[PDB]
Length: 353
Length: 5
Ligand SMILES: [Cl-]
Ligand SMILES: [Cl-]
Image (cartoon, rainbow over all chains, first blue to last red; front, side, top):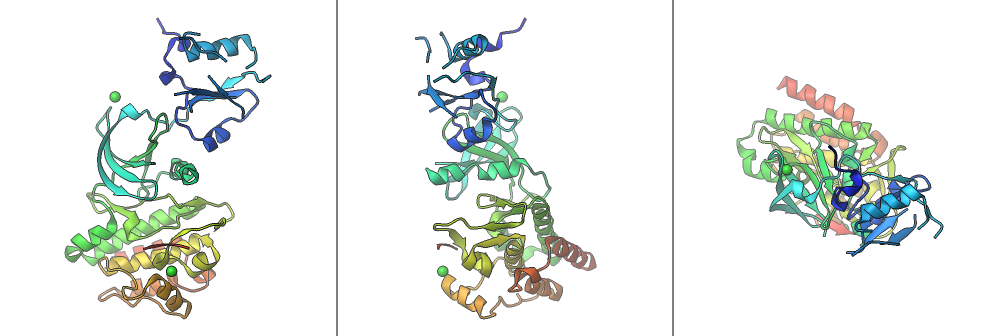
């Protein structure tokens, strides 16, 4: 026999979204009468009007209440229920994750290692410590839509409780900058060519998806135990059908020495500005992780670049890789190659080595 | 690396 749905605890209800932030509820409630329950404990019934809920009212439990309301079609306001809105397939309960030690940090806070309890899969877990707080789930919205060998995979989103997490594949060899600086001296150029080709494949993929990453750098690339490179940190990334993200107004956090002149000074972000950052990533790679413009401040770099200044060819960087960098740093965005062009050229270079 | 601008 079956336990009735309404007899199940609130925790188990498809229409209970726990720590769902404001902007999501907005996004989730489509038609008149659509509803969910969430925690504010004070539970809240969001039909977008928000009704605050040992018996619950506006019964022994909140599913008992919700069913009564639906069944009877009596009002809460005038507002009446039509259809409970379920969680999407990506929502994971906190208890399905075993949190491990911190492996990094960013603006929202720590990244941790973890495991999935059900099958021991190792994972990375981005946590969020409130306007910026509203931007946190951006990386999840973006990554839900993708699946590519050189892009970090989304596994799930823990929005049922605080603190909120975004759960991703763990790429166990760590960031590519540390990798270059720690293993680079034993690395063959052919391996380096493969790894920057991985990065180009990932970026070509992002451009096909109308995604503009905005923080491409060795520090935001990750290396598998087999030296496959995956692009990570999609926190600043934006999706634009028409291909340009226009910075919205207000202070911005800018990785100056990886940022194209037009993105920096006019706030025009595009796959073409991403190509500039790729140019810099190529430089980081074939320098075995040197810091770019090492004797210039950020301000001095902006001036040097505006005057036609560019990074020097790293020693023993193959000539065709440096020509490719140079092209990536063309001043006019229109003059830079596509990621398609870059990936093909890198594969061609690699094949010849 | 990052500048608030
Ligand atoms: Cl389990
Ligand atoms: Cl500056």
